Image (tube, rainbow, N blue to C red; front, side, top):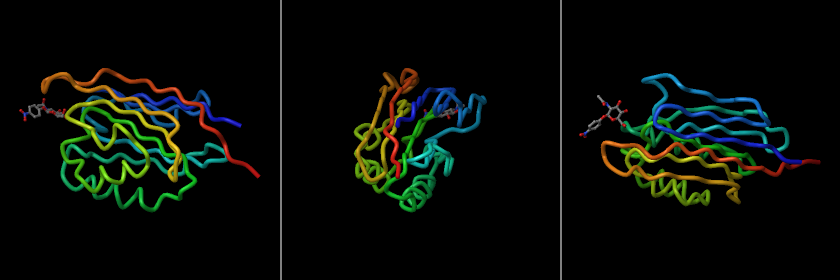
Length: 153
Ligand SMILES: CC(=O)N[C@H]1[C@H](Oc2ccc([N+](=O)[O-])cc2)O[C@H](CO)[C@@H](O)[C@@H]1O
């Protein structure tokens, strides 16, 4: 009646595991920058969608808003940052993250790391964030482990 979800965010690597199996893994050098988004079915944990939005670059946040607005309220939403996700994470995207109940997403800054798991229509199940300590540095890696309640019937 739960999913065991692990979410890792860091300078050089992201992964998401569901029930002990990796559903997203990106350790490649200069690829996959930005906010990775995974959508799960809330009864089975099956992956319904996997995206990456390079929100270090313009226009990617607008794509993220359009995509997230089409996700159904009951889905499990998972976000994780690789490298840098904030430079072009602008106010409409930050407001949308706030509407999910995210505390760190709306405040995401330069080279911060961030892991998030929540039901789209609420509540948030888990969240971790590490602030970069200097412009030339990254947040520390964060590994979030959350038991997500499953729906049924
Ligand atoms: C050449 C280089 O280091 N580029 C990196 C880039 O490095 C920067 C170095 C200096 C500045 N600056 O504005 O002074 C910006 C990015 O940072 C990006 C976000 O972390 C990285 O994705 C990118 O690989």
